[PDB]
Length: 127
Length: 103
Image 1 (spheres, each protein chain N blue to C red):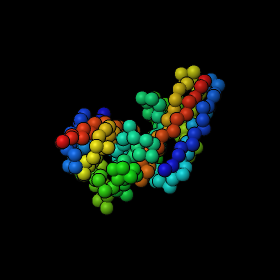
Image 2: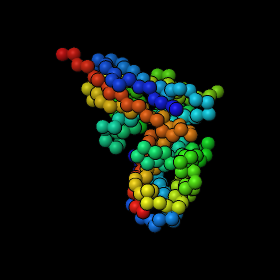
Image 3: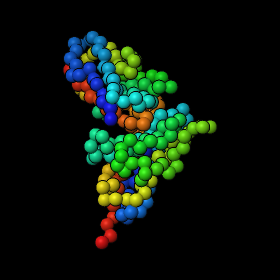
Image 4: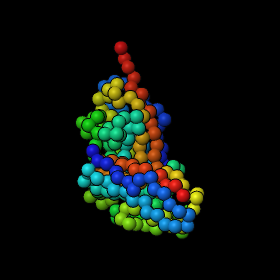
């Protein structure tokens, strides 16, 4: 019923800001998004969870790489009023060669369960 | 950051009952949701606010509890396989534990 819409590959220049789109579709009434988590499946155990968003608490960045300084949630908003976690688009400011890789966006929902989508980040090199 | 402890590689007899338990230690992260899953099958969900939810496919063979654990009732030889406890937490992220059951 519920699915994750993500781009298969996202290309971005070195140093520039890029967007990793993640959307939970279609909007189902009665379905509650308990958590949103961005993960790097290639990175080690202590560097898996790069970004997370809670409907009440808001955003958090557990991994120090890329960290809070280079990451941000584009449209995700917390409740103060109801929360909107449907749009899990992540922004990557100051792109480096280490950021090139796989990014899995996961939605912890009730009662449908867990739904995820994966995107490859292609860091373009100049000269 | 933190770690998940399991009941380990459990062994059971046909027709009986067994307990699948997981515990997240070495972190104070707010446990928003606990998912009891298999490779490509969802058994049960435990939400901190919305409560428990059991899949219709396991509604007559699974009991919720103890705590954030699962109770498998009337065990069949088909119940053999890997079981996963996925902990959705804030701010740490997503923790995963694996349990192998043999009937």
